[PDB]
Each structure stands twice: as C-alpha cells, then as structure tokens.
Length: 16
Image (cartoon, rainbow, N blue to C red; front, side, top):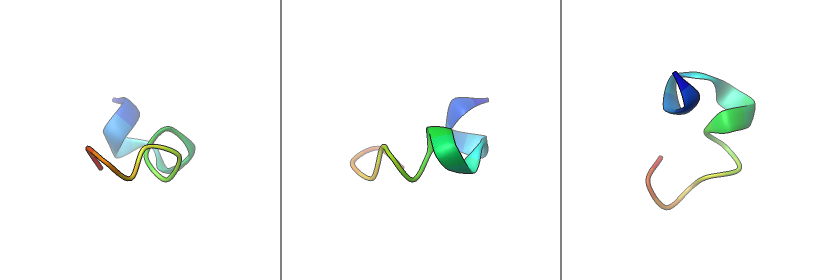
C-alpha cells in the first residue's frame, strides 16, 4: 500500500 506507506505517501501530497 503506497498511500499507506509514509515515503510512498509524503512524496505524493496530491492524492495523499
């Protein structure tokens, strides 16, 4: 889960 994983989330502040 990308959006559940901080590095895969914080770098993606548009969707997450």
